[PDB]
Amino acid sequence: ADGVGNSSGNWHCDSTWMGDRVTTTSTRTWALPTYNNHLYKQISSQSGASNDNHYFGYSTPWGYFDFNRFHCHFSPRDWQRLINNNWGFRPKRLNFKLFNIQ
Amino acid sequence: ADGVGNSSGNWHCDSTWMGDRVTTTSTRTWALPTYNNHLYKQISSQSGASNDNHYFGYSTPWGYFDFNRFHCHFSPRDWQRLINNNWGFRPKRLNFKLFNIQ
């Protein structure tokens, strides 16, 4: 889309309060290494662990983007503005973007 | 207008916040006596007073309605809502009513 030398996005970190809505936007810089050396590895609890700690699963070479915390979208001033003036809130919709990939 | 037995007004004490406006309404019950026994009396500073305290004026049999204080229109919760969220405020217009006169 933008080959080499053309930016594919802009930095949008801000919040807009409009009546009964607040739209919070956040931008961060991420680093993604190579996980498991491009391999899927079966993982399980160590031998000798207690029965409560036993588990079985798989480790993937993929990563994931997590923003399931309020601090990822609300500044402390935004939080104070939200909690001192509103009797409730709920999420409505979200937009996600990855850009400027090197 | 309402002769004897018909109310000439209602009790409106409340505040409405609408965007960049807040309208505060207050109703009070007042008592007005007879002042100076229906007379205008010349008044002046007492003899022997200091020069800084000397004055001359007149006392009238009339009363006056004063609402030149913020507590006359804003409840403490209204004041907290005003001062914790706004960088400024100013009055725009007012409406005054006397009713249910006995």
Image: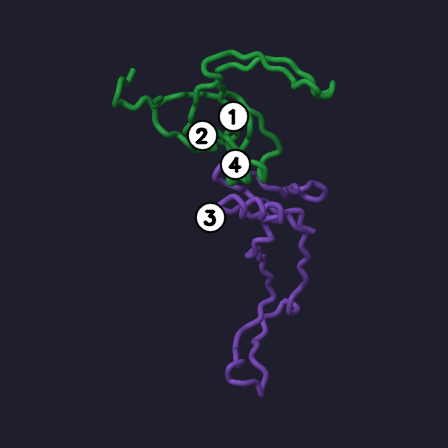
Chain colours: A green, B purple
Identity, as a three-letter code, of the amino acid under mark 3: Gly
Disc 4: host chain? B
> What is the spatial separation of the Cα atoms under label 1 and label 2, in whole angstroms?
10 Å
> What is the spatial separation of the Cα atoms under label 1 and label 3, in whole angstroms?
36 Å
| Contact flag, marks 3 and 2 (Cβ < 8 Å) | no
Is residue A45 placed above or below B4 in the rendered structure? above
Sequence-first disc among 1 and 2: 2
Disc 3: host chain? B
Disc 1 with disc 2 on a shared chain: yes
Q: Secondary structure at mark 3?
A: loop
- In the rendered image, which residue does mark 1 sit on? A67
- Asked whether, in this view, residue B43 is left or right of residue B92, the answer is right
- In the rendered image, which residue does mark 4 sit on? B18
- In the rendered image, which residue does mark 3 sit on? B88
Is residue A65 placed above or below B74 in the rendered structure? above
User: Residue drawn 58% across and 40% down?
Assistant: A84
User: Residue drawn 74% across and 18% down?
Assistant: A51
Disc 1: host chain? A
